[PDB]
Image (tube, grey):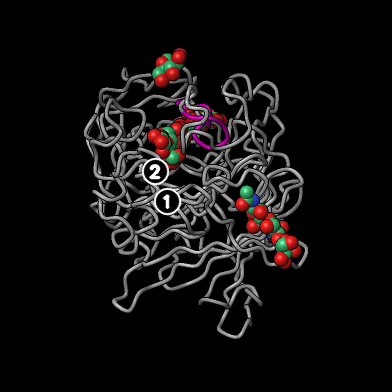
Amino acid sequence: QNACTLTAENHPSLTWSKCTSGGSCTSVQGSITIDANWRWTHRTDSATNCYEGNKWDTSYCSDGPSCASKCCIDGADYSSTYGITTSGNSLNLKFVTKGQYSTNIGSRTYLMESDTKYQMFQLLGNEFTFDVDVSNLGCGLNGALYFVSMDADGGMSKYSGNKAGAKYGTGYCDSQCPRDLKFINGEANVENWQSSTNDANAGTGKYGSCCSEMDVWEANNMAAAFTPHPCTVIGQSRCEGDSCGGTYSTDRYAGICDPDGCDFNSYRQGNKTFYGKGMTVDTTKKITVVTQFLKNSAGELSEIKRFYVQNGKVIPNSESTIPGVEGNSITQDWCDRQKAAFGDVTDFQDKGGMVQMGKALAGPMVLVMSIWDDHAVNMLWLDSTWPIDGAGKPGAERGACPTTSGVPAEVEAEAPNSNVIFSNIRFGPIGSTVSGL
Ligand SMILES: *[C@@H]1O[C@H](CO)[C@@H](O[C@@H]2O[C@H](CO)[C@@H](O[C@H]3O[C@H](CO)[C@@H](O)[C@H](O)[C@@H]3O)[C@H](O)[C@H]2NC(C)=O)[C@H](O)[C@H]1NC(C)=O
Ligand SMILES: OC[C@H]1O[C@@H](O[C@H]2[C@H](O)[C@@H](O)[C@H](O[C@H]3[C@H](O)[C@@H](O)[C@@H](O)O[C@@H]3CO)O[C@@H]2CO)[C@H](O)[C@@H](O)[C@@H]1O
Ligand SMILES: OC[C@H]1O[C@@H](O[C@H]2[C@H](O)[C@@H](O)[C@H](O[C@H]3[C@H](O)[C@@H](O)[C@@H](O)O[C@@H]3CO)O[C@@H]2CO)[C@H](O)[C@@H](O)[C@@H]1O
Ligand SMILES: *[C@H]1O[C@H](CO)[C@@H](O)[C@H](O)[C@@H]1O
């Protein structure tokens, strides 16, 4: 995709903290950019849309390279159009933003090191911490902070058709191999475009974009999970059609990434009073979330540990109480037992498990922060009973939301002013971001 400048692109600023062994932390001046799929896509020579509603203009261009050449993405009106604001080390993403001519739903954003480069993190062996407020995030919504193995420049150095780069939030990928991206590998995803049946702005193209994914945080004020998702190809790669896998496909496991992950949800692991409104981890208030990516002596990822801090008390992750799935952290062995007790597909195992996730964590990964609703499962996998008839079966109950919650059109209409606030990002070696773990 080319880049256009009918609208100035000014990344909202966002500071974060790099911490050293001993607890000393240094302020870093970063910023954030919005993902290209939310941007205006128009012809390079006019304001005429190349993509509008849920369609491409195929009277103008009709294949990947030519649309990538004749179309561009433009700047983004962060606050008034997308409901994205920052202040200091704090980022607020609003759910539905109604402007004069348009309605924006959700957002996906990336931390920048510079105007043209995502801030890369190498997580293995290290510690990542942030504060989050999910208090205004109800059933059916997901405020997500995670890492994916995108390239720092959005793919510019790999794909000559991508002339927009990280500045315009290009190059996305995750463990769902998403096919709704309008540009992948520097080529517009216009071939075999099929409009979504329930999302007025979306469709899927011939191609999807895969890469490793570490879901540090997927949460609302009812339920939370952290989930590694390995891929048999570590970095960004293009997939084709149904072989992409991911959930907007016929066989979600048919592709190269694990679409389920090895998930830890306190509620799903059997502790229903640990996380929620006024609970041990109280979701009406700001929560500090600590994640440690531990190595074994061979240098592989052996364990993911979670701690919470609220009002100065360190709260270790809740004990999983599912019989046979004892433990409060994610390990290969724990994941084997979890999949067994829940009767779930061992795709995590088949695609390389912890060791394969650690290969991604050893490399650079992009930090992404988003807010969204779910046009496939109404977020029931996160905060409800899933499958909907599975009450009493181990693994089915994930939160206390009703099985009728989460329908995008309904939650968009009822809770449009929902929002999530990510703030106070701290990163460094183990023990460096919060004292007294
Ligand atoms: C869900 O996770 C909760 C936090 O991990 C956990 O709360 C903990 O409950 C125990 C009760 O067994 C409390 O222990 C208190 O009582 C014992 C015995 O009287 C004392 O020896 C302890 O020192 C303590 O005072 C913990 O305080 C409490 N932890 C927190 C952080 O509140 C729940 O038990 C878990 N629920 C399930 C079903 O496992
Ligand atoms: O097309 C321009 C239009 O896009 C809207 O954002 C879309 C994104 O284009 C789309 O990628 C995203 O898809 C997410 C979906 O909503 C979720 O259910 C789930 O599947 O994850 C997807 C992202 O990976 O949906 C949004 C909403 O349709 C903007 O809201 C809009 O302002 C803009 O004009
Ligand atoms: O991230 C983008 C994509 O995520 C989809 O949700 C996934 C979850 O990420 C995934 O963890 C979950 O996996 C569950 C699985 O579906 C069930 O079979 C269960 O038994 O085990 C897993 C534990 O949760 O699946 C969902 C469904 O795909 C969103 O649906 C999608 O909208 C979004 O774009
Ligand atoms: C069209 O089809 C989608 C496929 O996921 C359904 O979920 C929905 O009913 C939409 O109307």
From the image, give the main secondary structure of the stretch colored magenta: loop
Which of the two residues, 167 or 131, is positioned nearer the viewer here?
131
Do we see residue 229 in this rendering?
Answer: yes
Mark 2 crowdedness (10 Å alpha carbons): few <14, some 14-19, many ≥20: some
Residue at the image point whose x is 66% and y is 63% from the top = 315
Q: Secondary structure at mark 1?
A: loop
Residue at the image point whose x is 47% and y is 56% from the top = 326
Looking at the image, the residue that sits furthest to the bottom is: 22
Q: Which residue is mark 1?
A: 324
Q: Secondary structure at mark 2?
A: helix
Disc 2 marks a residue whose amino acid type is Ala
The boundaries of the magenta stretch are 376-386
- Image quarter for ligand 1 equals bottom right
Residue 332 falls in image quadrant: bottom left
Contact, mark 2 vs mark 1 (Cβ under 8 Å): yes
Q: Which residue is mark 2?
A: 341
Residue at the image point whose x is 36% and y is 67% from the top = 301
